[PDB]
Image (tube, rainbow, N blue to C red):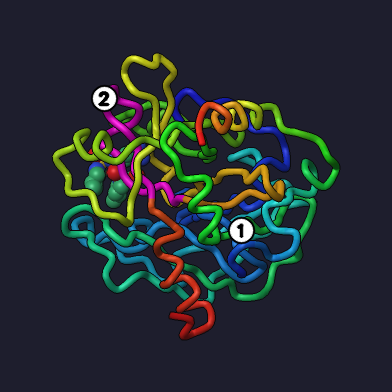
Amino acid sequence: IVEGQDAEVGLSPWQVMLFRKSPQELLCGASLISDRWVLTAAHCLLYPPWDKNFTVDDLLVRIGKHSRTRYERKVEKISMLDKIYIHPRYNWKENLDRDIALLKLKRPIELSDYIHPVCLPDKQTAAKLLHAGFKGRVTGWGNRRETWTTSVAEVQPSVLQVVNLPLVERPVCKASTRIRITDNMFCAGYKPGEGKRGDACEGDSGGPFVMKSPYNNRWYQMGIVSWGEGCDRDGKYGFYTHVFRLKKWIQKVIDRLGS
Amino acid sequence: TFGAGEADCGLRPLFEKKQVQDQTEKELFESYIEGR
Ligand SMILES: C[C@@H]1CCN(C(=O)[C@H](CCCNC(N)=[NH2+])NS(=O)(=O)c2cccc3c2NC[C@H](C)C3)[C@@H](C(=O)O)C1
């Protein structure tokens, strides 16, 4: 998270780390949307340009963490995925359209003071909260600046990072990029003149962009961290899987059919 | 999973349930009454 800050403890209790099993590395973020189900980005599992095509025993998931590094004994769950559901009209050969994936946990999680689901948006919360200039909340463990790498890229926070970042209006998301935008994605970030900064970066992808509804005091996940040209460049914005529109798919696969 | 609210969902045990606010929520509520 670029220009973010360390999160208080219990801040996104829905935050999930997507790790490779052996040898261990953090690959992506994801969120807990119930004691069985994790939403993350599709690019996290399958990116064919890069031969990435991860299966259920390449992968584990950690829940309830705050520090990136060391095992928080009392509070964290490692778990293995039972299944992996990637959208069929997911498009890796262009613009990462319909970039969403659902992961079925092996067994139910015991919910906790540090582990708790986030809600998916209804129609009305999408209608009331998705306006240009309204801010939502990205969190994650990824790099704090753009990098290449040396023997490691150096850029790894000890503790979970937060940034709050305003929704941006579509003809400016549009014109930020030569990439084809589709209604499945939105962008967010500060504009060159606004002189606040911040952005997801690598390793934050797959994670939640959440907004709090004042109406009921709940947090809703409106976005999944999808793609960027680099991290926090100016004149440039982060893009984000529009969860609500792909609510047709989500409820599909969870109820088997379901859409 | 449920849309709209799995009862306690998006109500964090350490924050809303203890009616404490986190260090950055007011920035968002700010952004709300900067718009509609
Ligand atoms: C394969 C995945 C695709 C998404 N990613 C990215 O988009 C990275 C990271 C940007 C982080 N900043 C941000 N989110 N604002 N930007 S990227 O390095 O320019 C790039 C790498 C490979 C594919 C693509 C990219 N650009 C957007 C394009 C539609 C898909 C990479 C990631 O690991 O996050 C690689």
> Left or right: where does residue A99 sit relative to residue A206?
left
> In the image, what residue type sits under mark 1?
Cys
Q: Which residue is mark 1?
A: A119
Res A120 quadrant in image = bottom right
Q: A135 above or below A205?
A: above
Residue at 47% x, 23% y is A3
Res A78 quadrant in image = bottom right
Q: Name the outermost residue toward the left.
A: A178
> In the image, what residue type sits under mark 2?
Gly
Question: Does the image show residue A25?
Answer: no
Res A187 quadrant in image = top left
Please report, as a chain letter, where disc 1 is located. A
Q: Residue A235's mark? A: 2
Q: Name the outermost residue toward the front.
A: B36
Residue A165: percent from the left, percent from the top? 47, 32
**Where is ligand 1, by quadrant?**
top left
A131 vs A20, nearest the viewer: A131
| Magenta run includes residue A225 | yes
Disc 1: CA contacts within 10 A as few (<14), some (14-19) or many (>=20): many
> Left or right: where does residue A17 sit relative to residue A114?
left
Circle 2 — which element? loop
| Magenta run includes residue A199 | no
Instruction: Report, in whole angstroms, how far the alpha carbon at label 2 lies from the one at label 1.
Output: 32 Å
Residue A7: percent from the left, percent from the top? 64, 32
